[PDB]
Picture 1: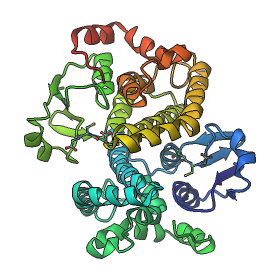
Picture 2: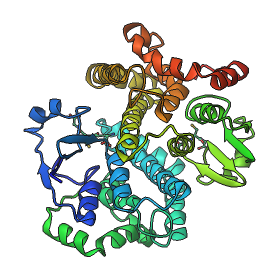
Picture 3: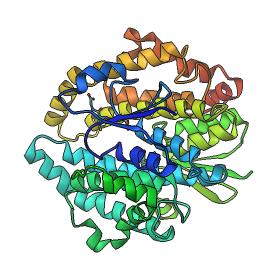
Length: 203
Length: 203
Ligand SMILES: N[C@@H](CCC(=O)N[C@@H](CS)C(=O)NCC(=O)O)C(=O)O
Ligand SMILES: N[C@@H](CCC(=O)N[C@@H](CS)C(=O)NCC(=O)O)C(=O)O
């Protein structure tokens, strides 16, 4: 199909779709829209945001919903309702970690940012990280089902952005499992080939 | 099946599952766990939080993932991948509105809460509400597909909690469409019967 993907020139919420498209052997226009040019595209999007995936002229918005749809098309969404559920479940936990980190990162008052961070360090982060370590260990380096699923692509796509927001670049020294879903996705030749060819960004 | 649902004695994130179970004609133990007793249940949950749905001893956590699963079991998740996608997409937009309201509501510093609110009033809320009004209008009073789906139950379950966080109890005076998904769910006899029999809470 004619496929076009629209997102900013970063990984953040959109890289997981690019990686999923690479997995599926689906060639696509990687439309990396600069901040300066974005406003001319914004009213053409379903909700006024990116990412947007366009397939034969039909637009799909909302990052996780797009990854789930691509995961289903590429056989990465489990074999029945209960398996599909587990992936949704573990990805929704990942989104809580992202949301908690985002609440610190996007605080523009450096003083309030500082107290929010301290508070999360003692009350949510330790529990999130131990829980993520349990899940990655239970699933042998994967986010769900003990094998490759679309949830590994969501994890791989957002991992650096998460780390940048957590302000622990050194996260995976205490938790070497945290690298494993990325390794699983980058082990896939097509995906490795796309990543080797693609720009790098810090988030 | 033997079904048990565990959540706090409020609607917030868990009411949508109770309503979906009522729709499905699935009798269940509505286990409303008080804050004071919660800690004894917390280590028995998959992630250390509620809601948790237990079916024949197997636990399902993560609210949206549970609603999607129940929606699929009850034929409320569309008829193909593209329809299922649209529901996921529009519910993920709803979650952004919730997340934005939550960032104000859970601010414990009343001064900072005040500036965050003012900032959202001029920069995200007007766009969210117009966009939600468009979606509800396009879909004839529903969150997606122009008909009843599991996304209407998510909306119905969280609507009061959202309003309490937005600090616009008067939301649906400017936007009478905002009441419609609730009307669609409450029009269903089993669901109306459960709601008539169930406790009321302000969120
Ligand atoms: N829930 C949406 C969130 C999308 C979102 O926040 N997009 C941001 C970038 S990561 C954006 O388009 N900002 C531009 C704007 O709002 O004008 C999704 O996951 O796709
Ligand atoms: N992403 C989870 C969030 C669950 C959540 O935040 N649960 C809260 C109540 S709404 C909770 O269990 N708080 C108790 C605690 O953390 O000890 C979901 O949607 O189910």
